[PDB]
Length: 269
Ligand SMILES: *CCC(=O)Nc1cc(-c2c[nH]c3ncnc(Nc4ccc(OCc5ccccn5)c(Cl)c4)c23)ccc1OCCO
Image 1 (cartoon, rainbow, N blue to C red):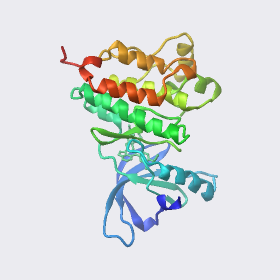
Image 2: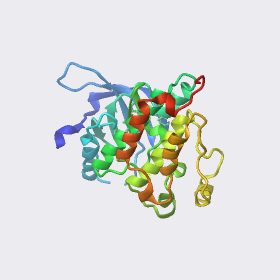
Image 3: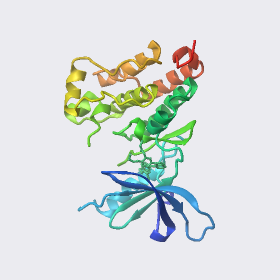
Image 4: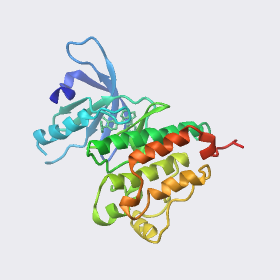
């Protein structure tokens, strides 16, 4: 369904400010100004670093998939511009990434917000699973905040993220929906610690020995045992014993209906 992806001319979008950068390239805030319309749409523009050598046709095939996602908790690719570089255009998410949001707001985040984010992320991942798409890089840095209670997963379809990876991904490069569930458990841990770094100060090459010994990320103080047990189930060595995203939607939706029962936040009780 080609109509879902706009092939953008260079005149149709303008990079105005920098949103962030790294080894991957640079993201800009700017405007999409479609020719023959009368509107200026706020967008993010991710310009990937120029590659020395896939051909346009293969890139467009993947971009068509990214433009085909239709779920309120998964970012959709709106347009692409292929030149010497690949530029990806999508709606601007004004509050930025969820990791930095929770760090910035760590004294002002309630239990219902936290649990709602867990529901929304599980819904987006369950959608990707229904589409037979494996994310491979779920993390709080790859959830974007459209408004404080509407978040969306980004950076699927595109430094190995060892500290978010299932053991079978580290050891055998196996990536499945169930290794995404492992990353989901780490992502929830990031939210419940208000953005702490997992395994802080531990070299990436030491993580597999931690997991092999049965050690895991610690129980966040605000988490009751019921919430931590979900997170621990996501880190089982047996991938098929981990929760499914459809079960995680159900369990976190139940907790979000009684948030004070399940998280004990600063000032509660
Ligand atoms: C947690 C740190 C961080 O990520 N900081 C950055 C935030 C943003 C950013 C801020 N507002 C945004 N709105 C919209 N998009 C982005 N970023 C963004 C991420 C991915 C992609 O393309 C990939 C993709 C598109 C569609 C579907 C699936 N994948 C785009 Cl186009 C835009 C926003 C930007 C950069 C940040 O820093 C990066 C380095 O830390």
